[PDB]
Image (tube, each protein chain N blue to C red):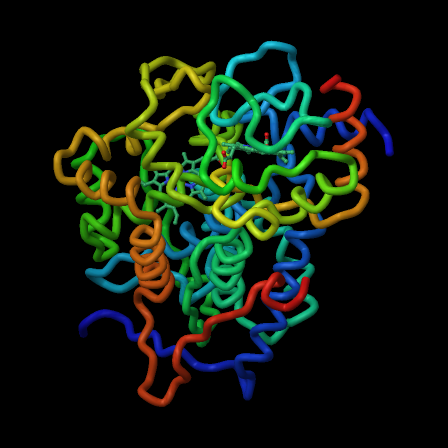
Amino acid sequence: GSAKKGATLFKARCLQCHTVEKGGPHKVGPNLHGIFGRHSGQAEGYSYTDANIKKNVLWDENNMSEYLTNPKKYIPGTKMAFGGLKKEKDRNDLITYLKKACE
Amino acid sequence: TTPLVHVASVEKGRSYEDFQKVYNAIALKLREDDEYDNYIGYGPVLVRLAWHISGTWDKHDNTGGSYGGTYRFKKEFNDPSNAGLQNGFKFLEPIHKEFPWISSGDLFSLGGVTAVQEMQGPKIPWRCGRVDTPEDTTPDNGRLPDADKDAGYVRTFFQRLNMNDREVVALMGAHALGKTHLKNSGYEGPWGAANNVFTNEFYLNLLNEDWKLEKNDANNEQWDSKSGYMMLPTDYSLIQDPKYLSIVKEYANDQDKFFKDFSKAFEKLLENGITFPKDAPSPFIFKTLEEQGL
Ligand code: HEC
Ligand code: HEM
């Protein structure tokens, strides 16, 4: 999708816990800078739960779309609570802005 | 003469299913107009509307309360402590046209029940029967709480709704949802990070953050944590009262518990002042969109 609509979707639903700046501070969640290619539970400087380190799954543009729809159904026992994107235009615009901001 | 008696009257031959349909409409639309307020959605505002329409109750003479769907009259609609709820009213007028049989009172409350369940809160039994009442039953403005107060105004404001300490602390956990808007109320900011999913964040934040009191732009003071959250005086007051503070700790520790007290309270809140004949149907438990494949 578009990168202009994905910039207002991340600064509204996320951002309060994650950050796209290189070397940012950890507020309530870990940093998403460099998330495409790393395993789940690899960010340093943050304590993860026992259900996020045991899954260990590579974050690609096909498996990350299922985690956005339901974060508690894909990974049972997660700590970050989030309703979940139920539209296909909101998941394609948020993944295009997370690939250009987190390089 | 004793107070007024408000008997719940089921809508002419309607039943669960007729009511699961209303839920679905509301529920879906929350799924559809998700852009509201920087993507918080209509969740927080509908739960706040539910609370305000019910919070006018006065147990001494039984006036106000959800029963009459009087929020629809200007007097009430225009109460300044009701600023921002017009956004919640609009969101359901459509759905009302769809189901013109349901009363106003039954719609405003079903709506808050939907929003809680739809945001992953606990299940909230609910009952129908509210009946619409003439413009004359409209409560004067001023029966709702002030934010700028302390534990003791809170304890007392609530005895008028007939709620105890545990019920008042549980209800307040709803402050996990949404945020304050300066144009609506003089305060600004969210209580937490997951503004649209129902957890006990409210209580962990209260006790784990570092609050500093400060003035906003509206010129009011509030407690701000470094992390970007805010707490109103009335919320902070919950940890300054020794008695409020142990309920707050319970809850920060055990979500199930919170989840169970909240549901008991929220429903008690919504049914206050209403008499259900012994022939009315047991309270309903509605299914979520998730539970229905959606
Ligand atoms: C707090 C309220 C958060 C909000 C809002 C969002 N995220 Fe989150 N995220 C948060 C935490 C505390 C954690 C770690 C949870 C744990 O159980 O340890 C996470 C985790 C993620 C992940 C996994 C990271 C990894 O495996 O390395 C992803 C992919 C992620 N979060 C993304 C994400 C998005 C896209 C959000 C909005 C839509 C979002 N988070 C909101 C904290 C919070
Ligand atoms: C002492 C009692 C209370 C006071 C003083 C109070 C005050 C406030 C204020 C000032 C706001 C923000 C208004 C705005 O800018 O729109 C607010 C928002 C809200 N209130 Fe409370 N509240 C009280 C109790 C409750 C209770 C008991 C509930 C619910 C069951 C509740 C639910 C909410 C929610 C969900 C929001 C967010 C709304 C949104 O995001 O638009 N409040 N409250």
